[PDB]
Amino acid sequence: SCVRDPSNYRDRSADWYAFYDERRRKEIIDIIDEHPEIVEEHAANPFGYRKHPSPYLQRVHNYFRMQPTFGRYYIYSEREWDAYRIATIREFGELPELGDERFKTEEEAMHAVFLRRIEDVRAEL
Amino acid sequence: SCVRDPSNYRDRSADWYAFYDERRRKEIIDIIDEHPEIVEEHAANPFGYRKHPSPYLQRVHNYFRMQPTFGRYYIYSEREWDAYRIATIREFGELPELGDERFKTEEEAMHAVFLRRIEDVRAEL
Amino acid sequence: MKDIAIRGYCDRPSVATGETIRFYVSANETRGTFDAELVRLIHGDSNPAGPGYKEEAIKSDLEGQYPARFQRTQFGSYVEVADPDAGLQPDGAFSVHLFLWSTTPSRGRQGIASRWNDERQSGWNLAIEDGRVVFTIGDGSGATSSVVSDRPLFQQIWYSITGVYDPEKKQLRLYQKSVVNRTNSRFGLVVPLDSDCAVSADATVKAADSETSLLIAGLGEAAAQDGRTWCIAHYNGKVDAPKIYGCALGQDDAEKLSRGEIVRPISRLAHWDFSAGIGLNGIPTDHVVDASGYGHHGRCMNQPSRGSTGWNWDGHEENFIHCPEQYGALWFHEDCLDDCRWEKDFEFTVPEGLKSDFYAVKIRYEDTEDYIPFFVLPPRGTATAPILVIASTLSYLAYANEQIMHKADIGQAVAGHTPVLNENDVELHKNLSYYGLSTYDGHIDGRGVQYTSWRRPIMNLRPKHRQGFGSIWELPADLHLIDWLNHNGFEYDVATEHDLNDQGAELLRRYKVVLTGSHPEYQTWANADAWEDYLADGGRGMYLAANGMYWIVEVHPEKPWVMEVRKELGVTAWEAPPGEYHYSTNGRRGGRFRGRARATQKIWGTGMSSFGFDHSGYFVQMPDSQDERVAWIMEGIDPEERIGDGGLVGGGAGGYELDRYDLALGTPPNTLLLASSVEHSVVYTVIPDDKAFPHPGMNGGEHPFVRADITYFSTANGGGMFATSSISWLGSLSWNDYDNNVSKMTKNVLNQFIKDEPAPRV
Amino acid sequence: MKDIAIRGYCDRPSVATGETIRFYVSANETRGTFDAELVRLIHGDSNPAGPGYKEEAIKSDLEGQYPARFQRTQFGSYVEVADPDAGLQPDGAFSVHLFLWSTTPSRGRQGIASRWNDERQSGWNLAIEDGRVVFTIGDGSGATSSVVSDRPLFQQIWYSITGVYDPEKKQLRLYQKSVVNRTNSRFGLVVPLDSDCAVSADATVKAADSETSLLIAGLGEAAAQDGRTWCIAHYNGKVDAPKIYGCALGQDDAEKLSRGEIVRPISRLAHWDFSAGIGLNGIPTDHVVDASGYGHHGRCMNQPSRGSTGWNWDGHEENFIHCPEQYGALWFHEDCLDDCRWEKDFEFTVPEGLKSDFYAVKIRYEDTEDYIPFFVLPPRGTATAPILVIASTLSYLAYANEQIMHKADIGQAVAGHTPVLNENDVELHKNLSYYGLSTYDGHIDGRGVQYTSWRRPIMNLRPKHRQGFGSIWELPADLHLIDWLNHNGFEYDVATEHDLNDQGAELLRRYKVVLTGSHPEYQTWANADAWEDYLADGGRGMYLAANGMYWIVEVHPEKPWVMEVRKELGVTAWEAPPGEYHYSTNGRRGGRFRGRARATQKIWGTGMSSFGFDHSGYFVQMPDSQDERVAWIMEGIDPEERIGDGGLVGGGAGGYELDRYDLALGTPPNTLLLASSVEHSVVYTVIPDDKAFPHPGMNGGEHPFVRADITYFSTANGGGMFATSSISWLGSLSWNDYDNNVSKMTKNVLNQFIKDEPAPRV
Amino acid sequence: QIWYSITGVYDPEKKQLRLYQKSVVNRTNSRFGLVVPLDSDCAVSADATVKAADSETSLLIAGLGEAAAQDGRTWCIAHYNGKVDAPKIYGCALGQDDAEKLSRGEIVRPISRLAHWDFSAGIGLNGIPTDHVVDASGYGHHGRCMNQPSRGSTG
Ligand SMILES: [Fe+3]
Ligand SMILES: [Fe+3]
C-alpha cells in the first residue's frame, strides 16, 4: 500500500452522482406523464402569486432549480419590460449563448425556460 | 414609561399561535375532504414501506407530528407483539390516560391514532 | 397497568479478572427479599421475525436472596459548606450578599442561600417566595421574622441582593438592584427597567443554630443525621460571588457591592469565589475556594454547570480559561443527578476463566424482572482472542434515561411515525427523581443537559428495552452483532470506550481486528487519537455503524463515572448559550469533531450525511464492486443483487442514520465506493452541517447527499478499514435465518481481517 | 449584445461640507473623451406599475469633458518586499525554505516565492508547474537552469520545501517533505502518504539581478517602472515562514527545517514571520516583520487572510491571539482585490448650501451611461433636519459585485424562480479582474470571501440595477424610502453606517428620529452599542426592514475602505474553516450577533425568522391593533383591512425576509404585536438558528416561525421603537399612487415621532 | 534528595506483597543530574501470611499512628523528613506496566482509585492559604495539614 501520485485517484462519488441523476430524470418524466395539468398550471402563474405550486410541480421545480450552474439556463433582459431571451451559463471570460426568440414579459420567458428544460430531459432519454 | 411588575406582561406571540392554529385546522379538514383516498392509503401502509406517503398525506402528517407533547397521543405496549393501547401524555408525576380498545399490531394502533386525531380536529370545528 | 417494583445500578461499567464491582438496588417499599443471579447476554431483540431473546445463566457467589429496601436519592445540584462549629451562624449583626440570575422565578419556593432547618424553622435563609426575594430568620420555636421585596424578579435578569440583620436597630433590611449590561441578561439597556428597592421589617426573634451545613441553591430539610444535610426547595438559575459579613451593612455598602467592590474585607466571615481554580486545563474539580481566608471551603453536589458566564460578562472573551473574572457564576437545576449515593447491596469479584463478554445481574422481585448490565475485560495487559468489540458506553451515557417522545415537540416529526413506548418510559415520566435526564433532554429551565452519570438506574440500557424510534437502540442493538459472532463461532474480547480512553492505542494494538458498535456517536479526543495511531501502524477496523465520532466528550478527571458534552448547531437536541462552549473538565472547545478539522471521513472513511426513522432502504452495487482488488469482499454475492432488503431495524440494511464518501472532509484518496443505499422518503433530511442556505426539497429522494456508502481502504504495514455507513446494518445480519448478502459480506471481511496475511492493497 | 464601455468609483462613500471626494474612471480602450455631471437620486426603480426613475441635475465645477483611458488593475493577493540594492539577490550559494499548503496544485503555473523578471527570465523563482514544485534560476539571456520534484503535490496537504543553489558543486537541489498532523491537512495520519523527495540538476547559468521586488505567492512580470512590480502567475493556498539563507543547505538542514528549527541563524539573509504583530487586538496591519534583523520588511497586497491556521496547528487553541506560534500562515487567492489603485480623473469639494442627500456622478461615453453614487453629510458637528436616514454602506459592501446566480448551485433554489439578469451581471462574469467578488461568493479555492472594498467599480450599487432575486436590492431599494419622503415634504439628513461607526451615539443624538434602510444586515459592535445608547436615553427609531444586525463586521483600522466578515452555520453563503473564526482586524469572535447574546430583538424588538423570494404576502391585524394605546399608529385604517396587498417588491408588504417577536431572544416585555404576514409558500424556510433536529415541513404555511411581526415599544425619556419586520415594506409605500395602508401607517408613526411630545407610553 | 516513584501492592489471590521503585531524576529536580549513571530501580516480591486489619486510626502522610485514636486524636510518630508528591490508593492489585505508567505521571485505572490527594489543588493568584488537602478521586476523603508543612514546594 502506497499513495505517491495524485493522478492515480479521483472523486469516486461522481459514480453515485451519475447513477442518482439518471434515476431522477426517469422520475421527472414519469411525473409530467402522470400529471400533465402541472405544465398548464405553470403557464397560468409561474411565481405562484396567491396560487401556490402543486406538490408535483414543486417536485419538478426542486429537481430543476438545484442543477450545476455550468450549462444552466437563465433569462437575459435585452430591453427592460420589452424584450427577454434565454441565456446559457458558460466558463468565466465567455459571453452567454442567447436564444433567437424574444419574450414580451419575464413570466413568458420563465414558462419557455420550463418547457425547454422538459424537452432537454426528454432528448437525453 | 416604566417596567416594574412582571404580572403586567405576557408572551403576546400566543395571540399569533391561536390565529395560526385555527387556520391550519381549517386547512387540514379541507385536504381530508378534497383527498379522501389518503385515509385508506394510511390504512394500507402507515410506515410508507416501499410505498412513500402522498404529498397531501405528508402535509397532514407534518401538521400532526409537530404538536405540543402535553395532550398528544402515543402507543402503549401492554403486551409485546400482542396488545397495544392509545395513551395521552400528561404532567410529570401523572400516569397516561389509556384507551379501552386493544390492538393486535402496532400498524393498526398507528391508523387508529390517525383516525382519532382527525375526529378530534373535526370535534373542535 | 404493569408498574416497576425494583431498580438498580453498578459503580463502574467494566471490570477485569480479580477486580470487584459493587451493585446498588432500591424497591418501592422496604418489604420482603429479591433474587439475584448472573447471566451472559446474547440477543436482546424479541422480534418474532428474528432469533428472539437469548441469555446464558452462569454459576457465581453473587447468586442468592437479599433484603429489598427503599433508598432515597438527593436530586438537583447545589453547593454544601460543612460548618461543624456553627462559624457561619453569627450571634450578632450579619449580612449576606450575592448576584442572582433566576430562570423560573415563579416556580414555587426556591432557597437561594441558607443555614436553615425547615423542620424546626431555625437559622437564616434567603429564598424566592411568590416570585419575590425574602430574607428570613428563626429561633426554632416555630416563630420566624421575614423581610419581603416589593419588586418581583424578572426572568433571566442579573440582580445584586443584600440581606441584613441589625439587632441594635432590631431590624431586617433587603437591598435589590438590577445590574443588566449589553450581553449578560435576557433583554438589553433599551428596556426602562425599575426593579431596585430598599425594604425594612421588625426583627422579633434571634437566629438559632440550625444544626445543618450552609447551602447555595437550596434549604436544609432537618438536623443532619450521620453528617448528611438533605437539600430541599431547589433553586433554578445562576449564583455569582456569595459572601457573609459579621456586621450590619448600609445602603452605600450595598451600592458598592452591586458594582463588584469587596467592601470591609476584614469583616467577611466567608466569601466563595466559584472562578477560583480556573487554569489552562479548565476547572476539573468540585472544590469551592473560600476567598475570605477562614477555610469555609464548599463542595459542588450533583454537578452544577462550572465555567458559566457571570454578572459582569461583557462578551469581549468567550473562553472562560482566558477571562476567569467574568466566569464566576454557577448554574443550578432542580433536576441534576451525578450519583444516586445508595448503600451497596452486594459485590462481585471476577474469577479466573470467566470469558470477556457482555454480562448482567438478573433480579426477580414480586412479578418484576430487572437487569444490571456490565462488561468483563480480559486479564490486565493481555488479550484472549484475535477480535476486539468496543461497547459504546459514552453513547450509552449520552442516551441514558432518554425522554424525547415525552418532552421534545419534534420527537415524533423526527421519528416519522407515532412512537411505541413501554412501562420503562412511563416509569421515567412518573418518577424523574429516581433516574435523571439524558443529554437529548433539556432541564426545567430550558438549557440542554451537559452532564450524564453511570451511577444511576438506566432503564434504556437493559437488553429487553424497545426505543421510541420504532425498534431497539444502543446496547440491545449492539447485541445484534454479539449474537451473530456467537452464531458463527468467532472468538472475540470486549472493551468499553472508557477502557479505550484510559489505555489508548496499546489496548487496540493487542488485536488483529477491532469492531465498533451500532452507534459510536460520542468519543473523546484521546479515542480519536488512539484509533488514528492503531489504523496508521497496520491495525484493521470494521465500522458497522453510522454517525460515529460526531460529538467530542470529556470524562471527568475526579469522577470517571461522569461524562460532559456541550452541543452546538448541527444534528443536535439543543445549542449551548453564548460564551459557554468550552468544557469545564479540560478547558477545550468541544462540540462537533467536524468543526475541529477531525471529521469521521479522516479516520473511518465515511461521515454523517442524513437521518430518518420511518423505515430503512437497501444497497445498490456501484462499479467498484466489480473491481478485481475487492473480489474477496463481494465473494458469493451475485453482481445484480440488492444488499439488505429486509431486517429487524426498519426492514433494511441502509437506514436510521447514513454516512457518505467525501474527499473534502478527509476520505483517503485510495478509498473505493462499493454500494449506495436507496428508497429514502421525505422523512430523511440533509444535516445542517451540509447547508449554506436552506431551500425546498433538501430530503430523501430529492438531494444527492441523502445516502449510505459502503467503503474500504488500506493503510501501511498490512492494515485496512471497512465501513457500511448504516445503523440498521447489524439489524439485517440474522435476516432469513442468517442467509443474506449482509451476513456474507460481513463474514468475508472478518475472515480476511483475522488471517496472518496483510489486508489487501487498494 | 449591449456591453459596458466605461466604469468608475470614488475613494470614500460619504463627504461633509468643504471636504473633497476623488473619482477614478477606466474605459475599454484609450480614445476620445467622456462627459461628467452631478445628479441627486430620488427613485431608482423603473417598474411601469410605480413612479419610475427620478433624478435632479445639479450645477457644479465637476460638470465637463475628461479624456477616457484604460487603467490596469492588479488582481490577486501576495506579499511584496522592496529590495532596491538587490540584497535578496545573492552572488554565491543560497537556499530558500518555506511551508506550503496548495488548494489548486494543477491550475497552471503558480509562483510560490521569487525575485524574478519573467520578460527577461532573470533572477530566481520557486513555482508550481504541471502540479510539481520547480526551483529555477536565469541570467537574463533567455537561458535558465531548473530542478523539478518527482512527487506531484496533493491538494491541501502541508509540505516543507527547500531549494538550494550550490555553485561549488555547480548544482540545483530540491527537498520536499509532507508534515501532515491530525488537524492541519485535508486527510489524516491513516493515509500511507509517500510525497518525500531529494532531487538534483546541473546549474549551467548564474542568477542575475531581476530589477524587481521579491514576491510571496507570485512572479514579477517585468522590470519595475516608477517603483511598481506587477505580480503574475498568482498562487492559491497558504504560505508559512518563508526564509532565504546565504549558504548551500544539506539534507540534515532540510530535515531540521521541516520540524520548525531555525538552523544556522547567523546565515539568514531574510526571514518573514507572518505571526509577528499578533496581540490582544489581533493583527490590524499589512506590515510583515523581517525576523532575521536585516530590515527586509514586506507589505501584504490585496488583503491576504491573516490569522490563518499554520503548518504546526494541533487544534488545542482556536483563537489566534492566544496561540500566535501556530497561526504563522497567510492564505493567498488569485481573485482578491482591496483597491483598484487607479489614477484620479477629477475631484469634488462640497460647497455651502448643498443639502445632505443621495448623490451620483453621471458619466456619458459612446452610447454607455454610468453612475458613481456617494452621500453628502451635513456640516461637521451640526444637524439640518429632525429626521436622519442611515445608508446601509456595510451591507452595500457585503453584496458588492454579487454573482450568486452565476456561481452558487442553490442560487435559483433560494430565489424560487428563474433569475432575470442584465448587462451588469454579464459584464461581471466576462471581466472578473476589473470588479472582484462579493462576501456571498467563494474564491476559486472554495473558501468564502472575507474582505470587501469600496475602492472598486460596484455595478449593483447604481440606481438603475435590477437584482437576481426578481426585483431591486440594497441602494435602489433604499431609494423607495427617499422618494416617499420627498413626495411627503419631510425634511431629512443622510449618514452612512461608516459615519455611525466613527461618530457613535453622538451622531444619532442630534435627531428626533432615525430611519434604517431596507436591509441593515451588516453592522459593527460599536453600531449596536450606539443604537442601544441612543434608544435608551429617549431616542426614536423606525426599523422599516428585516434581517438587521445579523452579521458582526469590523472596519479595517489602517484601510477604512476595507470591511471584514467571517461567517458560520446559519443564514450564510459559506462556513469559516476550523480555527479561523476570529477577525484579524480586532482579534474578537464575530459571526452572528445572536451567537454573542445580542440578537436583533434585544435592540429593535424583532429578529430574523425566514427568507423566500418567489413573491411577497400581506399583513393581517392582531388584537393589539385594537388597543387604545396604539390608536395613533392605526388611525385612518379600517380594523378589517389587509395591510400591503400589492407592491413593487414581490407584490406585497410582508415578503423577501421576515422578522418575528421573541421574548427569549430579548424582545422588551412591554412590546405590542400589531399584525402578522401570511400567504408564504414552501420557498420560505425556517432559518438554521431556530432548528435543533431538521424535520419535514419546516417552511412557509407549515411552521409557526415563518411570519413577519409589526411591533412597537417605548423607552425612558419619551423614546420609542417601531418595526415592520419586512424587506418588501418600502416596496409598498408608493402602491396605488401613494394611497394604501402601508403609506398611512408609516406617515402616522413618522408624524408622531417628529413632534415635541414624548413618544406614547406602552 | 533524589526523586523516586514508589508502588506497594497487596495481592491476596497470589498471596503476595510487591514493591516497585524507580528513579525519576531530571535536570533540575534532584541533588545530582542525568550525568550520574544511577541504578536504583527494583521490583521485589515477598509471601503475605497475614491480612490487613482495621488499625482504628486516621490515615497519615509522613508518619505512623502510635495507638488507637482516643477522643478522635491520632498521635503521629516516626516522622518523615523530605517531600511527598501525589499519594494515591487503588482498590486492585497493580502490575509492572501500571507502576511504569504511574512513574511517568499518568493516572492509571481512574475508576479503581479509593483516594488521590492532589497537594496543588487550591493554588490561585493569591497562593494556597489553607490546610485543606483535596481528594481528587471524588470520594471525599479530604486531608488536613498539621504543624504547617511547606506548601508551594517544587515537585
Ligand atoms: Fe445521536
Ligand atoms: Fe444577506
Image (cartoon, coloured by chain):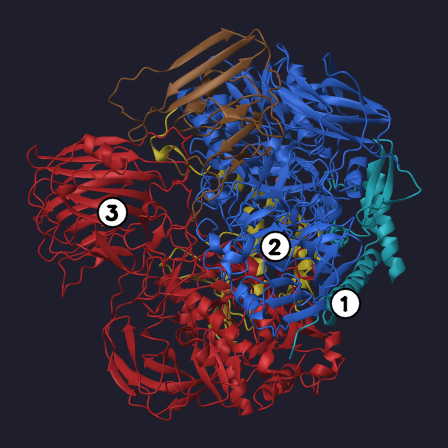
Chain colours: A yellow, B cyan, C blue, D red, E brown
Residue beneath the point at 27% across and 60% down: D286
C-alpha separation, residue under disc 3 versus residue under disc 2:
54 Å
D184 shown above or below D223: above
Residue under pointer 1: B19
Mark 3 vs mark 2: same chain?
Answer: no
C-alpha separation, residue under disc 3 versus residue under disc 1:
63 Å
Percent coordinates x, y for residue C290 in the rendering: 53, 48
Residue under pointer 3: D112
Mark 2 crowdedness (10 Å alpha carbons): few <14, some 14-19, many ≥20: many
Residues under numbered marks 3 and 2 in contact, where contact means CB atoms less than 8 Å apart: no
Q: Name the residue type under label 1.
A: Phe
Discs 2/1, front: 2
E81 shown above or below C254: above
Percent coordinates x, y for residue C67 in the rendering: 81, 24
Q: Name the residue type under label 3.
A: Ile
Chain for disc number 3: D
Q: Identify which residue, D733 or A36, lies in the foreground.
A: D733
Residue A65 in view of the camera: yes
Percent coordinates x, y for residue C439 in the rendering: 64, 43
